[PDB]
Image 1 (cartoon, rainbow, N blue to C red):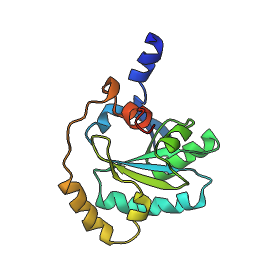
Image 2 (cartoon, rainbow, N blue to C red):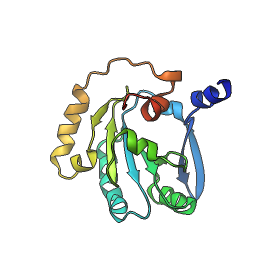
Image 3 (cartoon, rainbow, N blue to C red):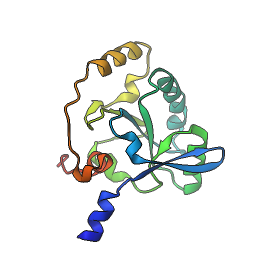
Image 4 (cartoon, rainbow, N blue to C red):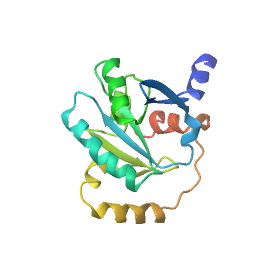
Length: 168
């Protein structure tokens, strides 16, 4: 149990990103108390690639929402090229079907907005960000959202977000 739970306490302790052809990492603690935008995608997914343009517009208007790529690339080579092209933070290249199942994600691309306490602010944020009324409406939604304190298992926000049992 000890070895397994030490791994859980350390689960997702780094997120990754590219910077001038160089793979970098950041402590997951940086994301504590931040709104997140979870982008489920893959290099081989035509409309995931075009969706990058929508995410760039989103980041311009919501710079403090941290975009995290949840990858479904076929190869690590595609994963690296996707990170280099988008400059998004990303989960390490791995199998994330379990995240799809937990959130009932039906297809790619998908985009979900997550509150600092791991609630779903907008489930289908890919459709939210299609037309221009979203900008002021989302500013209002974030401004008005009341964040009630939540303690996460292992004090690990990503373990709670991706590994809690509440979907059952």
